Picture 1 (tube, rainbow, N blue to C red):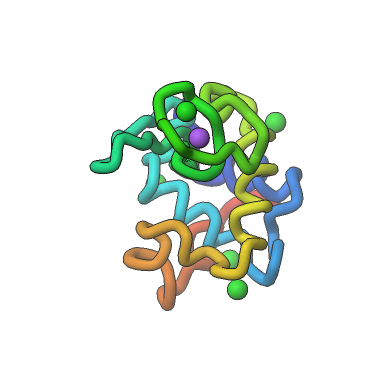
Picture 2 (cartoon, helix red, strand yellow; picture 1 turned 90 degrees about the horizontal axis):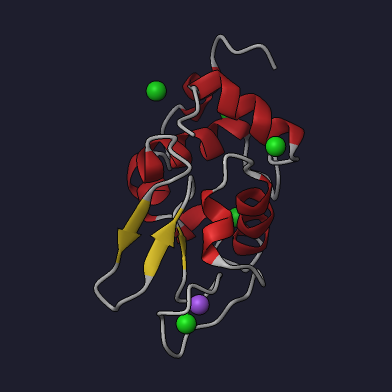
Length: 129
Ligand SMILES: [Cl-]
Ligand SMILES: [Cl-]
Ligand SMILES: [Cl-]
Ligand SMILES: [Cl-]
Ligand SMILES: [Cl-]
Ligand code: NA
């Protein structure tokens, strides 16, 4: 599923990401835009053999099991394929664990390089929330 900008904002709000650990909703929408272009089915392989999955490009090296990342962890206790669903619940719940682990949203390279320090409120401007 390719979300629209305001559609995704509303879904993330319903699932409790607005101001979660202090990060306003626009931060999460911006991260999703540049990680996946709002596409729940996005995948990308990393140099070390791990793979990033879904609208927030969560990494199999630490967070989910895909059966092909030897020596990795599965800290969200989910198969990585569950992060590709049109229902974003699994991605959101895993992202909550990630952002709570001490490094905040700096875990998302695209957030750090393209969202951090910008006017992220523009990502939810005009949306009915
Ligand atoms: Cl957009
Ligand atoms: Cl915001
Ligand atoms: Cl594995
Ligand atoms: Cl949902
Ligand atoms: Cl933080
Ligand atoms: Na893994």
